[PDB]
Amino acid sequence: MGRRKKMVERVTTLMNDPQRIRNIGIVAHIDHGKTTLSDNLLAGAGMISKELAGKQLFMDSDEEEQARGITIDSSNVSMVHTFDNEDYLINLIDTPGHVDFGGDVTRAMRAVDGAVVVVDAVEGTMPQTETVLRQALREHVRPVLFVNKVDRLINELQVDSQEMQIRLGKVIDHVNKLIKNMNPEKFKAGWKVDAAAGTVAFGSALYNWAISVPMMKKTGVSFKDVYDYCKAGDMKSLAEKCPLHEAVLDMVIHFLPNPIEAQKGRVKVIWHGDENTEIGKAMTHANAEGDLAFMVTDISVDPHAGEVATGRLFSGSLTRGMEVFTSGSARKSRVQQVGIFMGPERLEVDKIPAGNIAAVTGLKEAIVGSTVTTLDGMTPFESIRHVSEPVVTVAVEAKHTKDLPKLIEVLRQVAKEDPTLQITLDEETGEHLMAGMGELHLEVIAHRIERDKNVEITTSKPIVVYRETIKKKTEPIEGKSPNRHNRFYIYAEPLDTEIVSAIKEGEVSMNLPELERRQKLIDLGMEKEEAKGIVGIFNSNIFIDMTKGIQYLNETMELVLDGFEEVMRAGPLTREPVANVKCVLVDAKLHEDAIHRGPAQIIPAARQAIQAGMLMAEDSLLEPYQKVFVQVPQLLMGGATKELQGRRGIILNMTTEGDLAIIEARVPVAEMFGFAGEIRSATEGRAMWSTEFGGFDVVPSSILNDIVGQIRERKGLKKELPKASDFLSM
Amino acid sequence: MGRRKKMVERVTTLMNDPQRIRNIGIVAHIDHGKTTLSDNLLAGAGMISKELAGKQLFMDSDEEEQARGITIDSSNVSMVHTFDNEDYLINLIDTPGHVDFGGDVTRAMRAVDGAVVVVDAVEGTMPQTETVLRQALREHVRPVLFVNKVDRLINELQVDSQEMQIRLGKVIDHVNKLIKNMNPEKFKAGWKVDAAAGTVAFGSALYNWAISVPMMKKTGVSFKDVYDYCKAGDMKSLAEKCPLHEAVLDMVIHFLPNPIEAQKGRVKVIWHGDENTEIGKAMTHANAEGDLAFMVTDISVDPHAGEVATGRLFSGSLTRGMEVFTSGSARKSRVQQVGIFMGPERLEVDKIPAGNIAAVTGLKEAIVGSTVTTLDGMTPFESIRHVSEPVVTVAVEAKHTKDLPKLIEVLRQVAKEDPTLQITLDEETGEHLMAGMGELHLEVIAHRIERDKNVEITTSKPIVVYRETIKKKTEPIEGKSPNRHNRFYIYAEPLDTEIVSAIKEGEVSMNLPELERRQKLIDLGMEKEEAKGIVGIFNSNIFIDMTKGIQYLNETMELVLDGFEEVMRAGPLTREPVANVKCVLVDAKLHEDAIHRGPAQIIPAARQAIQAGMLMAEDSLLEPYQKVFVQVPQLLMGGATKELQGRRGIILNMTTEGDLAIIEARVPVAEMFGFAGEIRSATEGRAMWSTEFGGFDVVPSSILNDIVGQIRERKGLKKELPKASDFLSM
Amino acid sequence: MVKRALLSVSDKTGITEFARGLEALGVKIISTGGTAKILRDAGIEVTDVSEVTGYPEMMGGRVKTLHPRIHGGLLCLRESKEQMEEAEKEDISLIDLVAVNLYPFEITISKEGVELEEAIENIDIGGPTLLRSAAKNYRSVTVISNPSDYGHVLKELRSSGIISDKTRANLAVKAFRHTA
Amino acid sequence: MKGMRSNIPRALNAGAQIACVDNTGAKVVEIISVKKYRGVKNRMPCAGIGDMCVVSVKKGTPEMRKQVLLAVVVRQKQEFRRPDGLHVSFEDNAMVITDEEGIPKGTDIKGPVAREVAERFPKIGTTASIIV
Amino acid sequence: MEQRKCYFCGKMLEPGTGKLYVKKDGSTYFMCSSKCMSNFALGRLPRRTEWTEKGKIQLKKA
RNA sequence: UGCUUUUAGUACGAGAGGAACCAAGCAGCGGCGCCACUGGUGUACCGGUUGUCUGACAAGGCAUCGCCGGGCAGCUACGC
């Protein structure tokens, strides 16, 4: 009955003991001491045989954070502190709240009961801190204050005890003052901290010492005594006398909520589906017997055990084995192994009930944005999606001629390094057209290149990737094979935006049972006839064979759909991929034999026809937008708003949360250039901006010819408009 | 410092502690939970954390052994028992207690210095028991009797205390008779046993109680009392104060000779080399020295571990990074895993001077029974080869056409079980040519088939296959082309026996320096020119290119070679594989162009010629022999030998030692059928034969006609064959 | 330019020199079977097809080889991404010169009846494919079918540096013709 | 850089074609220049064990060839003295491809490396099978 | 102070002198002098060279 | 006159990034000297051997020191 094994059983007891769970977390500004605190906490309560941790950064169970000194992303660990003769399972949400994160922040915060704001004892409350704190609070995540790095003040800056507490007081003040401006209603529900109320600790993670007003009294150790030990090299004594884990875990349990309680207000704030719905009541008031709620927030792909998705068991008991679903991607995958997280590793256990992050393997429907469920079509906390493709490309060159090889390999790694780009690695010209998702993303990656690999290279003017689009319903255009033995009367017309969206969603596929697919389309809008006569879907294009009784078309098909996909990949105008285009085949005159129906004859006719049609139907361009979110001060809104408005900023919300004017708008990607700069420049450096693919939109006809010409030139094309006339040759 | 966590520490240095080291074995009968008491010696007796010790019979490196009442193969471990306040390293290397186990048993005994006895109550010195005592006597492995579970005699059969142990007093006397009669000299040399003197124990392995006069006294529970306690029914509580392990261990330390003593003993008899080199000295007179004098007892492995070839460090030292040769070639591999079989596995380490075990890994090409040592192994222990194949198989059938499917898995799979069963599994009619060379091999698999899967099949009679060859140097035969354009004058002749043996060993490799190979050939005897012209070798036949001048020939080599190869697969006389035949291209005459040089013209010519050559060269046939090691009881020789000689068996050694006449005679497989059958009458039912592929020799010329005749019809071939001229049809 | 060369030539006539040349111009020689042998017995280092495809060896001298999914790399442009990438995949190579001739078929007549079985047996299946594949590359890969054009090739390379389009054309056509 | 315990004569000067002894695909590399080496008039750039040189891959794979890379010499035939007075010499010269920081591009190093390079760049030591 | 033996003549390397020679296969040989190094590089064997200890051992084998 | 370690991932900075005084070692070039060590040379010397002459053996002449191998002192640097 090893100490570890007894703890293991304890672990299971606590698992089925929701009242004794504390899914806490750590929230702080860069280089404040996150990783430090974390790991030294683990070792502080000695959950594992001490040595085990430290050297092998545990909390940093991944590989990036493992060389920083401050937490970066998600995962979790566990502590079991004894408080007034009682143990409590303390899950330790890793913190993906580093400024270099958007949705991830949210995701984790929607799995964190409460957190611990860690404020450098010197540098005080910082921008980062502000951002994280306000965010978390918005998503209802009560924190406590652990001012770390006191050691610095005490020794380095040789401050005196009295001053020590004056400074810390001023910090406490700042802390709450912000909390106030964040949410007065929550500041009225007394979440605000104060060390006298035990919700604030004082210590140094790097030295594992830490005190707090309560413990202080309990043990007799006062701020002045602390100062004495510190000045007299007695930080060892400090640590021993008043452990770091001690103070922290006290705040973490005595004043931080458990699954149940947390879940209540959490569901009320984050979730939007009617709380009377079963799933609702289940995850609100602690219930795992109801519809499975397991929003995967991490995919610990165990190299020797497969994809291990780590999500918080908001609802859904984990009895061994369960065929289920998920949010959005609610398909039909199962649930095999469901290990809990002991230390930083995966301890395999059976049934896990409520508020207990579990790692589940054998889960195809399981990634970020997907809340694994056993009730199909599960309601959403915050709506999510899944599509995201390169829209802003740059032509990464290699100035330094003695770098090409290196470059080649560096971007050959960039693929998995950050799965959001699609470099067109070439040798013809040497210009690696890296296609990123955002001008900022691009800039960031490019910078990372000559920094972590340091290839003396740069990137040239970013360009927007558009789509080719038709305007109206066309008139049957004859597509003739060279030998004239085949004629393909075909027309096209805009693809119904509804259908567009759902196809990009992926549900509608060509690998779908007739009935199944057809229905969807039918209601979405596709006229029954067409829905029944579809034969292919490409991005946002379809080739609806609407003809009947044409000999040899059944077989012929392939070659025509080939031409179709070709033309769709590059439209006759701006040579850009076609999007939102649905073709209707109306007649198919064919020669009897296949001799005069070989691909070399079929493919041309189809191609020719489709292109000519597109052009006759006022071919436009689709410009992607990019939903902007500007977390800025209240005050700051004059220049900000005018800026976006001048940049076609369709404001869809402005959330003027007390002292913060968090404007949420939508601005065209092409026009997002420069915005980065101007926003902060004008707003005196006070503008935390963030964006995300706002969906392709029918480019304002205003200067369509202009944009077109630009593209034409850049991609070296002809100056005579590609008149449909020629395409529909004799 | 969790049990084995401490052991690890002590062990790492214990390596160079011969004084306390105890590498020993266990020999007796089966069905006496002998391998189970040895499971409990260390794994049972929790030599690691109890959870990770003997819980799931993991002790033995060869995990599969589990427990059947005796060793399965030669698995290894270690146990640091305390005796008179001292932690002796009793490396448990329990030796296989069977008889079939042979050339490998030799080294499976060399791995230890004392095989130990275990005989359950009134089981007695079974035939097998005495057989392993005989094998023990060879490798100078002193034994100690361990009469297991006397419970039978006790509780079940109730034989009064005194009687009870008097029966064993006699059994002990029989073990003395064994160590007298068999080898009289052996006795006094420590091999003597006795309960009184302490060199003999007893006790139920399954109940874990156990005692022996030393134990008996020390514990205060004399054997009489123990009987009373057993009888009563408290054998478990007895076990408690008389730990099954303890006894054994106690004796290994005290009574059972510490390795050092008979460190020499084994070597001389077991080792076939110079027992007086640095290595020899060390291995004998307990020392380290001997440049990494490891012995590949059994090439092993382990998942993500190493080729854990076993070999107790009978001399030398271990370290990570030693270019170690082998007893087959000079592989030279990094020896990362120089660890010690410990806990329930093989604790991988490095610093291990001579004393304990020494299983080295890092290899993948040696043989079970090698002696891998950095030192240039002149004559390592089992300096042997392995080049062999079964040549008298059968035609596994199917009594029921419904088992065929099953049979299919059964047989295709069996390869896994045993790769020595080259299951020439035909596919059409399905006369499955299940491997074999003798009656042994036949039944060997017989049961396997009808036991590890169980099928309703059967067998036919011995497939009397051999190897075709010739015996006379011929005169250049011309092999013309189909299109009568080309020609090749090839001669054929016997392949010299030295050369034969050479390539039978394999050393003469195609992937080998010409110059080098050339010398070797000349060495053997083939003159310079001829020896240099050698192009290729198939099976055990060589094609020599001793031509000069023919243009565009090496561009044809391919074809000609293949031609040769083809013939080598199918004899020109009996349509049987050809071996030990040297073929030499003298002249040739190819057509100028390439059109008239295609395979269809070349290949025939070559085939034709080579074949005819063989015919004219007094083509005979070879026949495998099988060395019959027959351990007939010493006395018995007249009949024993008579049998073999009568079956045309060229008598070899009589091996008369103590009471054991091992008369080998390399009995021709021809008449090597129903050996046991004959034995049971010839030697009044008393003889233990065992066979091994003696090698390919010449079938008695006298009976050639007969042999051929048979073969011809057995396959289904015309009685007469294309006599010379006809096959050489011009 | 030629960087790697697949020399699976049934007829070996004069391959030794072509090989020597290429090696001297760096061109790695990825060959197997008869050729491979001769080359390694003539002081020319040659890598084996094993270190390209995932296909070992069997009846070296005719087929034993082929290249699916992957032939599409050399195909009609061993540099055209969509084309290119296919042949080089996992340890595979971007050979830009393949020379595969085919021993002329012949049935003949044996002493005991037409040798149909073996005679027909030797219908090169790998070879022809490699040819057609490479051949299609009117660009990139320079196919060398006919053995009596190693000179021309070598000379051009040794001088110019790149087998001109004209040449590439002639060669490719000739290959297709050979398979015909 | 960190000082070595031994005194190393800079034995290989610019233009030397050294065998490359890792699994990167470079068989022979010619020294172009020596990093952190300032010369004098008429003196060729010189490199001994432990020095990092800019090299051009002359033999090897076609992807490696003609590339300007960084290499570290691990074996040199010119004798160098250890601090305790013993002179060490290898049978040949040998280099391994690395980056600026000293990390080897290869994964295993065939042949013995010098203890001097093994200590100056610890990753070369771990990559090498034996350090002499 | 490492005590080293000349591979050719079998003499102890005096501290502060002598050479260590390493082959490609990692084989290491101590040489007491340029004479021993030259004789080793000539392919001569110590057992055949009379002034060395291995030559003396080979001769006294008779 | 550089590199590396330290100061210090600190000041500074929202981050990214990222110093300075002091201290240590090493290196490049230069200067001066030295020869225990290592390398070169070493037409002192020792040996092997080819052709030829002194009749043979032995001992010698000549052929670049005939050539080949080794090399003490001395000088020297590629060494200190």
Image: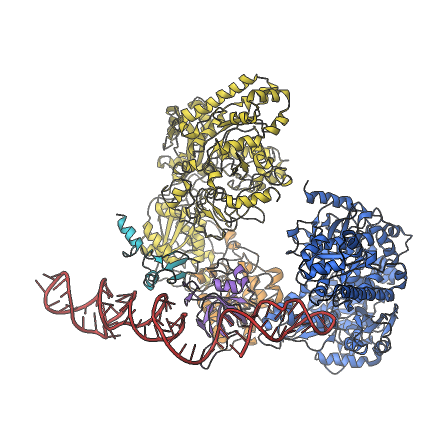
Chain colours: A blue, B yellow, C orange, D purple, E cyan, F red
Above or below, C121 against A420 in this view is above
Asked whether residue A202 appears in the rendered view, the answer is: no
User: Which quarter of the figure is the N terminus of chain B placed in?
Assistant: top right
Q: Which residue ends up furthest to the bottom in the rendered image?
A: A719
Above or below, B498 against A251 in this view is above
Above or below, F80 against C67 in this view is below
Residue A147 quadrant: bottom right
Residue A619 lies, in percent from the top left, at: 80, 75
Residue F70 lies, in percent from the top left, at: 30, 65
Name the residue nearer the viewer: C161 or A149: A149
Residue A599 quadrant: bottom right
Name the residue nearer the viewer: A119 or C64: A119
Above or below, A190 against C165 in this view is above
Residue B512 lies, in percent from the top left, at: 41, 56
Residue D117 lies, in percent from the top left, at: 50, 64
Q: Residue at x 79, y 49 (%)?
A: A21
Name the residue nearer the viewer: B1 or A628: B1
Judged left or right of residue A473, residue B685 is left
Name the residue nearer the viewer: B514 or D75: D75
Judged left or right of residue C142, residue A702 is right
Judged left or right of residue D16, residue A698 is right
Callout count: 0
Residue A245 quadrant: bottom right
Asked whether residue A198 appears in the rendered view, the answer is: yes
